[PDB]
Image (cartoon, coloured by chain):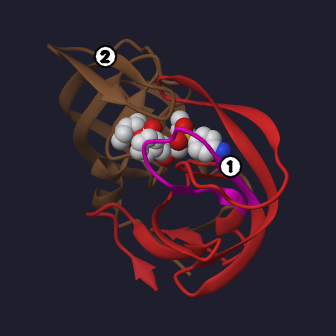
Chain colours: A brown, B red
Amino acid sequence: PQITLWKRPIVTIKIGGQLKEALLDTGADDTIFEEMNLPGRWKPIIIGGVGGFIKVRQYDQILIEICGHKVIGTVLVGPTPINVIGRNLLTQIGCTLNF
Amino acid sequence: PQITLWKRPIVTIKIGGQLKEALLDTGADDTIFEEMNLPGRWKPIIIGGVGGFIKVRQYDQILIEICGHKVIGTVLVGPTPINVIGRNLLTQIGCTLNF
Ligand SMILES: CC(C)CN(C[C@@H](O)[C@H](Cc1ccccc1)NC(=O)O[C@H]1CO[C@H]2OCC[C@H]21)S(=O)(=O)c1ccc(N)cc1
């Protein structure tokens, strides 16, 4: 699909058996999700944004289905104000900016 | 241009007679720039992102040239770690996500 930006480019995704919505964020190097029940081991991680830093848990090789497109990559889980699909996963679906 | 996302989608822009680099950020509703003494009046504003909120100065109807494309819109000035072109200006150059 081609997505214009008059509204937030929020898409439907499937992750860890749960249904969720996430923001296609080209400004996000990596994917981050609000608190959620993922399986497996994880490592504490500290990320940064406009307002400062938050502590999150990094999970690797996580299967996501982004708007019917499957991808496997790192997914951080922590106190983000919204679920964000970062460039680490956008590249796998072949996402591009156009103008 | 069509921009892939293996690298940060950073473009060269002209603002207030100054040259700067900024991130094409579909996750940003509005444009935010590091400190710069733009001319004119402004109104205090508080925005929020990952890690909390920051206080910024809001200027309206500011001319930016994004990759040689002129646009006029709101530009926030404050302690952001990186210049971000938000959706308020991306729509004016017709920027879209494609995959
Ligand atoms: C919560 C986000 C969806 C909103 N943000 C845009 C987003 O692209 C920021 C923009 C951004 C970019 C660099 C530094 C700070 C903020 N990226 C970001 O927070 O990235 C962090 C979370 O995922 C990781 O990816 C790399 C950094 C981590 S935001 O910078 O806070 C923002 C909010 C409101 C406006 N008007 C403009 C920008």
Residue drawn at x 44%, y 51% as measured from the top left: A27
Write down the quadrant of residue B59 in the picture: bottom right
- Neighbour tally class for label 1: few under 14, some 14-19, many 20 plus, Cα within 10 Å: many
For the image, the number of numbered tags is 2
- Neighbour tally class for label 2: few under 14, some 14-19, many 20 plus, Cα within 10 Å: some
Residue drawn at x 26%, y 63% as measured from the top left: B6
Q: Is residue B5 at all visible to an observer of this figure? A: yes
Q: Which amino acid type is shown beneath numbered disc 1?
A: Leu
Residue drawn at x 68%, y 49% as measured from the top left: B76
Specify whether tag 1 is near ligand 1 (CB below 8 Å).
Answer: yes
Residue B7 included in the magenta stretch of the image: no
Task: Check the residue under mark 1 and report the chain it is in.
Answer: B
* Residue for badge 1: B76
Mark sitting on residue A38:
2
Write down the quadrant of residue B54 in the picture: top right
A98 up-or-down from A61: above or below: below
